[PDB]
Image: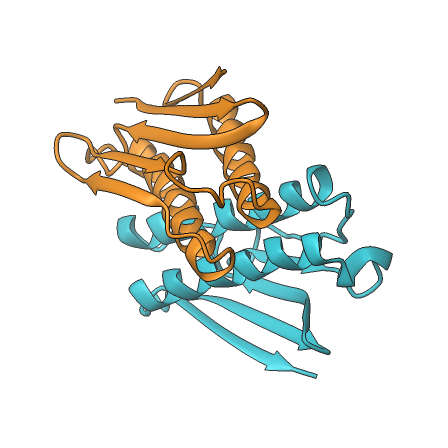
Chain colours: A orange, B cyan
Amino acid sequence: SMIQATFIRRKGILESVELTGHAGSGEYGFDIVCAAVSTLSMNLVNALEVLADCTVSLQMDEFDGGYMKIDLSYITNKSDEKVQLLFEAFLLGITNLAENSPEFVTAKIMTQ
Amino acid sequence: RGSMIQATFIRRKGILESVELTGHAGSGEYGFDIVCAAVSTLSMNLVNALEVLADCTVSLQMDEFDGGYMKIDLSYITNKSDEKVQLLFEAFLLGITNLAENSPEFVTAKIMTQ
């Protein structure tokens, strides 16, 4: 069991993220890390709404090891410091977890 | 048994300055741990995001023992009123808030202002 995280930073700013494999896999040591991923995942989507007045493009489910995509491409708000500052903390949170448990987590970043 | 983590937020003058976390570390069963893993992540993230992105260093304090004890404090950090610092903190308050809402039996949070 492994969680896959891919961020997309276009010209210096975070645009989207496409996490997969979280949303449990009854494997405790893993489910632990999944909780972690999901906590950070939903907080972003929430804090971005509540605190940044940004309603991101969300897509999700907990089927076959869950899949969740958060897009900001179709939004001319993504450049708001408050949006970007929050997205950066999410990248900083996912990044540390994939380096603390490279066994369970993988964080990639495509720059363009 | 008696599995409960509490988030005590103090807000002095419109801005958050500290928060205390006790019990979030250690066991209680499976579902409890999951919550602990969630609080500890949001908690460790705030400390890291504040130092790295927020240019603000924080007074930390923890004893893995006795349920676990966290105390992220900003009462004496010059830039504590700084808006970057406050946004990241606000969101930490939002995360901890829903997490306590979704799992009332494992997490409790209060905000007492001064």
Q: Residue furthest front?
A: A76
Question: Is residue B61 at all visible to an observer of this figure?
Answer: no
Q: Nearer the viewer, residue A57 or A18?
A: A57
Nearest the eye: B81 or B23: B81
Disc count in the image? 0
Q: Is residue B80 above or below residue B47?
A: below
Q: Is residue A79 above or below residue A7?
A: below
User: Vertical placement of A19 versus B76: above or below?
Assistant: above
**Screen quadrant of the N terminus of chain B:** bottom left
> Where is the C terminus of chain B found, in terms of image quarters?
bottom right
Residue B11: quadrant of the picture: bottom right
**Left or right of B90, for residue A23:** left
Q: Position of residue B19 (x, y in %)?
A: 62, 65
Q: Looking at the image, which is closer to me, B101 or A52?
A: A52
Q: Is residue B1 above or below residue A62?
A: below
* Place of residue A26 in the rendered image (x, y in percent of width and height, measured from the top left): 19, 36
Residue A77 in view here: yes
Rendering quarter of residue B68? bottom right
For the point 49% across and 46% down, which residue is it? A77
Q: Residue at x 31, y 43 (%)?
A: A57
Residue A100, horizontal then vertical, whole percent: 51, 26
Q: Residue furthest bottom?
A: B114
- In this rendering, would A112 be left or right of B2? right
Q: Position of residue A40 (x, y in %)?
A: 43, 44
